[PDB]
Amino acid sequence: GVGISTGTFNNQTEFKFLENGWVEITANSSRLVHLNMPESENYRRVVVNNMDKTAVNGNMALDDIHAQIVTPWSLVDANAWGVWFNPGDWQLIVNTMSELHLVSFEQEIFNVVLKTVSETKVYNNDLTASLMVALDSNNTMPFTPAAMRSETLGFYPWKPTIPTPWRYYFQWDRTLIPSHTGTSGTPTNIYHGTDPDDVQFYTIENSVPVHLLRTGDEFATGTFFFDCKPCRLTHTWQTNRALGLPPFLNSLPQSEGATNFGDIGVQQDKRRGVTQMGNTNYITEATIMRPAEVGYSAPYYSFEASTQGPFKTPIAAGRADGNPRYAFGRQHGQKTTTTGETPERFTYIAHQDTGRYPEGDWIQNINFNLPVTNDNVLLPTDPIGGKTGINYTNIFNTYGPLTALNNVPPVYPNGQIWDKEFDTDLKPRLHVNAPFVCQNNCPGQLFVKVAPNLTNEYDPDASANMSRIVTYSDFWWKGKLVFKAKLRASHTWNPIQQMSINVDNQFNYVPSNIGGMKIVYEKSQLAPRKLY
Amino acid sequence: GVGISTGTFNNQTEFKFLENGWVEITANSSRLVHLNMPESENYRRVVVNNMDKTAVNGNMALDDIHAQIVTPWSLVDANAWGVWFNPGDWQLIVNTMSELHLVSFEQEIFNVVLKTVSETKVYNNDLTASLMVALDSNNTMPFTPAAMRSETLGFYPWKPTIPTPWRYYFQWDRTLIPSHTGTSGTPTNIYHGTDPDDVQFYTIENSVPVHLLRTGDEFATGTFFFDCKPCRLTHTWQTNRALGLPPFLNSLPQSEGATNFGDIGVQQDKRRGVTQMGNTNYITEATIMRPAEVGYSAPYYSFEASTQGPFKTPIAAGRADGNPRYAFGRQHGQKTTTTGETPERFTYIAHQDTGRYPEGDWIQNINFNLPVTNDNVLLPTDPIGGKTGINYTNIFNTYGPLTALNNVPPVYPNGQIWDKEFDTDLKPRLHVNAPFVCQNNCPGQLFVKVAPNLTNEYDPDASANMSRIVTYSDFWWKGKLVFKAKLRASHTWNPIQQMSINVDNQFNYVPSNIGGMKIVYEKSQLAPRKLY
Amino acid sequence: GVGISTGTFNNQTEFKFLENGWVEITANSSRLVHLNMPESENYRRVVVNNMDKTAVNGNMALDDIHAQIVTPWSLVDANAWGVWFNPGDWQLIVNTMSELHLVSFEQEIFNVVLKTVSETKVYNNDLTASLMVALDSNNTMPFTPAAMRSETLGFYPWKPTIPTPWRYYFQWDRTLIPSHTGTSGTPTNIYHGTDPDDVQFYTIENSVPVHLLRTGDEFATGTFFFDCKPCRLTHTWQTNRALGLPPFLNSLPQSEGATNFGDIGVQQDKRRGVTQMGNTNYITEATIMRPAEVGYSAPYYSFEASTQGPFKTPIAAGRADGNPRYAFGRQHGQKTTTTGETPERFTYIAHQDTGRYPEGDWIQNINFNLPVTNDNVLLPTDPIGGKTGINYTNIFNTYGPLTALNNVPPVYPNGQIWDKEFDTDLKPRLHVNAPFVCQNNCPGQLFVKVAPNLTNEYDPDASANMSRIVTYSDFWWKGKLVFKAKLRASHTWNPIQQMSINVDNQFNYVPSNIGGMKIVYEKSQLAPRKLY
Amino acid sequence: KAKLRASHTWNPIQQMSINVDNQFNYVPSNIGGMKIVYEKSQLAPRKLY
């Protein structure tokens, strides 16, 4: 009954090598999850509004108006790389593997303990009390991944963790007409309420079965099996200038040295080749016809509005703009013995050259008078709209049928692993937040909640909140994430870039004298691959 | 023989309930189709040229220039929702069923009657004459959905209807350089004839078989079978702002009313999460990363020109830009007792929030100093090219690899049901005119004509038009259009928007004192669905 | 054995007729290939840096700065139409076929002869020397289509050819800030070096097994089988204005001649139809709701900057911009008896009307008042950014989900046949340079070299380059390429445009007085096809 | 019953084609005026000996 344990701790990573070059990587994780009771048992609808700061002109991007259903439940989320892989295993994966397939995911809650607090304080075991656990096997609830806010389980096996109090967006209608510093007057800035057509009030109790676990009980999610396409751990460097056959060089440097360039022998208007410029005889590396377009230029720092307020248009890649910035706390990589409230931050400067350098772009007139006059070219120095700070590249969009693009790299430790595909009829080609996209269904979210230990005084017909015995739970969570990965091959003569310890990064990977630990970010897409 | 009927009028619709929550909806439609003989038996080539109205400057958008091959044949087109379902049936579909598939379509012409007019007028039956009937099973003829002109069969089972006189576009070449009022001089508004490379002249006689039905026998089309992807009768509300985990709220409200907002606890630069703004520490609902972009800004009221003159660039989702405006006559929904040429009109404001609100958009500089100065933000108040009426969002496109979109909702009664997919090598994601799109083949267009009932005076070598006995026919047409649809389930606590008779809309659904009838538009995506 | 011949020349085209209107076209091509020894045996990294030309302001598009590995091997590339089909066979293909599949490809080297030169010049057979032959079956090396540079095998069977010296792009980092004439000073124009993360050095010696052929031996590339989607040899004349049912004409013309137009009978504001304009009652051929968008506008002559320097952003289809312009030499179509270095050129004006006419574009305000005032309309004549030459259509992009597009047409003789699909995670819709794209694997590149005939004086410790017995090889190359094409059917009444000989082009196709030859370009997509 | 031809020679042969001159012989007029014009039956050359 009470006295017998209900599952073994396990945080080992198993590397089951197979011939034909594949490895089945089984990341086991376990944590002690601590769960206080809810602040209130009721479901609440809370409207956030920050007109106190957004109504100041120019602060348009600081909009936080939204409506959310704050729930009495907490969510246990393992959807982040740091939950599964320590730095050494991640080093092995990035340094040796070439592509990475996510295979399966499973979860267990075991060794549940329930304790009452009495008050000096004394702690009493509630052998009769119970922990509610619910699995959204059918994904009826809104998908609410916690890595976006840095609220997943902790990344250290030996520290307890806490689950995030769960909430989801309710519908609101809001408009915020933008304005600059020195605008003549107060812009239109109001919250409209909500549309009856879009009301969606979800509850765990009506949506999913809820298991009650006392002390001896276990909950075990059966193995979810993914079908996701591979993530590739090797970046592409070939931009459009470096696709295809280079021009033949007649003048080769006959004294080997840095300053001794080679020269194409033939004048620029007398070369052979193909250009996509029907009226231009000059064949140059800028003009010559490549097969297609790598990357695309996007309107950078463009905010677009609809019924629920303004939001940034996301970008697939960056040079800066576009590169993601992760801000995170002490459970998720910041040095655990820091005292401050300020989060740790990095921006992931990805290796891949799919981005654009907008300071070098231009458009010039169709006539192509070659040493261009001012009237025949539009540069990034030139205004648009009369504004000196905004140039044409800010409003430019060169996505097209010829665009080629890469899926987003995995960002260790804070980045997501999987994401649910949109229910839209026309589905986005990639997601900017996760490398793998569940196409048909995704793993069930796991919700937890400690039951009400009522006092003797309860009367449902009283207006006041129900009195509850102050209770908390600690339960051990375990999970197993299976990947299938391909080992790399040495195509080139030269060696590749590899993650390695060095004198600078040495003390990031080991604990300090007073016990503190950190996890620095480590790049994934290290080895180069041919684009074409 | 002559006196035996050859078919049953049937305008019922059965709902056949299959296992596992599917309903096979069999829509039967029957119509008495009345057909006058053609104005001329010869195929004509006619150029329309409103140079007079487009030469006055500013009237560029009123360009009606086209060439077409006026044809003796007439087309029976049943490709509109109103031909099949009445308002009660449409209510039962949309209020209760979540997705809808096409299954099959078939047609029958039966009970042909031929009559001749002689001068007072005496009407006499011609048992020897024949209705010429042709089916383009192979889709060799140019496709012409009659819904875009509101020339489908009538939507009332009792009234007789008429088929559309058939015609199809011919080649032509045109240039219309645009011009505002107050332009110095006349633009080059000229018609260049037809490219010989592009000539296609089609005739029913040379292309498809033809059946000479007479009064005593039927024509029947085999059961065509669709393979289209499901149209979904439910709408998505979630803007980018409403995807993912909302921020945690630390100060929940303690009293009722709209004044009691809840507040996020920590300062915007000390919050935690993932933004896609590498140089910016502010994490806000506008700046926080989302999986992908729902909807896209498109350059609104952009007219774009090809060899065949200007046309509007279509837009996939409206907010009134984008939303379709239907103009229709007394066969097809207008109150039949009204006088006057003027059509009735509605604009279909769809429920879905995949649109944009252009006045709220803005673009600002990479540096992102927070209270943005005038020189550093381009607003919709700012003129492109010095034109005060044309702000940047008119000339602005944000389609990209992250755009997600829904298919167009069904529009009742005038919207198309199915559409033929293009024979392009690269095919569009969606068609803006119908929910279902035929992937490889589509239902054959049914062409009808009455044979030349000649007089004794005929001489083919005479230049003048042939003398014909004035003939007309009535033939009963029977269609059967089968759907398969899934019954909805109540996942939310709250109820959904539903179509209902009420005191306002009551008398739209019953005939008037002198028997006038109308069919109002009814919204096809009522129940909300979970995008993420 | 030395003297036994090891193959047979074959340059025939067999048209083999299958069931159901298919034709298996077996193009055989045979050439004599002449290969001198490499200039030096070592691999050379060379950087081209033409700062002398581009440091002059406005010479931005003349950027030729790049790095490459100059490799001693030479590439034998048959990837062009002229290598396989002569003008008569191409006439038969374009005039009689409708779609053209690509089936298989195989290669052979046979009748190798090696010779050496001794000083008058004496030519001596090298019975013991060998020709190195290497097939990259796995595509380890970068794909390198020689047709982009016009360095394929020559198109005349009776004339010898030389293979291209192989080279491939190394990585380089570059910034080139653009400038117009009379910019204040020298802008940033610098070569940064190479990123170590992107270095890739490939040797044929390590990546492929190298065969050694002396004289009596052969190498036969086994049959590679493609899986490419079909190329269509018909062109789409319909643009958006010619999709759907034309408006009904009440006023048909009653007399002959182009100056007797027909007229639509109903005023534009009392006209039935559908429009994507919620606030506009005017239904007209510009505004009527078409199914989708055939073609798209793109920013014309837009140059975009990557990490490696500016490049021309490509366009899918042209009207001009977008139409490819070829420059080609004596082996590849120019008059073979001409003096001078200048290449022969053509611009391939494709027959398909999917392109745009930017001078006909206009954008007008959402209110849509008809005689548009200057402030409410933006025209292609209006300046943007204060520049008079550049207008909004240079910045504009209409690409959206509704875009439909055609694949790149074949260009006879200088265009490619196949190209390798990019290894990116999201791949382009089409390629602008080859009609067929290999889906997963593409036929192996064949690299050839003559092995070193060292002198007796060789010493690897010597500072100077090695000494070699001057040697060269002639080897006969044969290839077989199989297509599968569908014969056309005469759907129209009218004849189609067809390739023909006539008095203007008569002496292009037959040799001249002193034996000169040329191959004039021939258009592929002749017969019209209907989209809709 | 007819035999499809074969391209024996290097050069392109004469072929029947629509062009700017003969275009409106093969499509009707304003008032249904229709015509058919003579088209040459024998176009490809043949080696007699």
Image: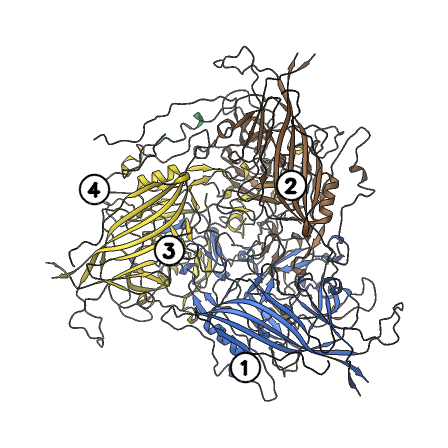
Chain colours: A blue, B brown, C yellow, D green
Q: Amino acid at mark 4?
A: Gly
Left or right: B168 with respect to C229? right
Q: Which mark is residue A284?
A: 3
Q: Is residue B238 above or below residue A26?
A: above
Judging by the rendered image, the residue that carries numbered circle 1 is A508
Q: CA distance from mark 4 to mark 2?
A: 71 Å
| SS for callout 4 | loop
Q: Is residue B444 visible?
A: yes
The spot of residue A19 in percent (x, y) is 44, 70
Give the foreground label among 3 and 1: 1
- Comparing A434 with C275, the one in front is A434
Mark 3 residue crowding within 10 angstroms, few (<14) / some (14–19) / many (20+): many
Q: Amino acid at mark 1?
A: Asn
- Comparing C241 with C139, the one in front is C139
Q: CA distance from mark 3 to mark 4?
A: 34 Å
Which residue is found at the position 81% from the left and 37% from the top? B507
Judging by the rendered image, the residue that carries numbered circle 4 is C515
| SS for callout 1 | helix
Judging by the rendered image, the residue that carries numbered circle 2 is B482
The spot of residue A186 in percent (x, y) is 73, 58
Give the foreground label among 3 and 2: 2
Residues at marks 3 and 2 touching, judged by CB atoms closer than 8 Å: no
Q: Amino acid at mark 2?
A: Val
Q: Earlier in the sequence, mark 3 or mark 1?
A: 3
Residues at marks 1 and 4 touching, judged by CB atoms closer than 8 Å: no
Q: Amino acid at mark 3?
A: Thr
Q: The N terminus of chain A appears in which quarter of the rendering?
A: bottom right
| SS for callout 2 | strand
Q: The C terminus of chain A appears in which quarter of the rendering?
A: bottom left
Q: Is residue C171 above or below residue C527?
A: below
Residues at marks 3 and 4 touching, judged by CB atoms closer than 8 Å: no
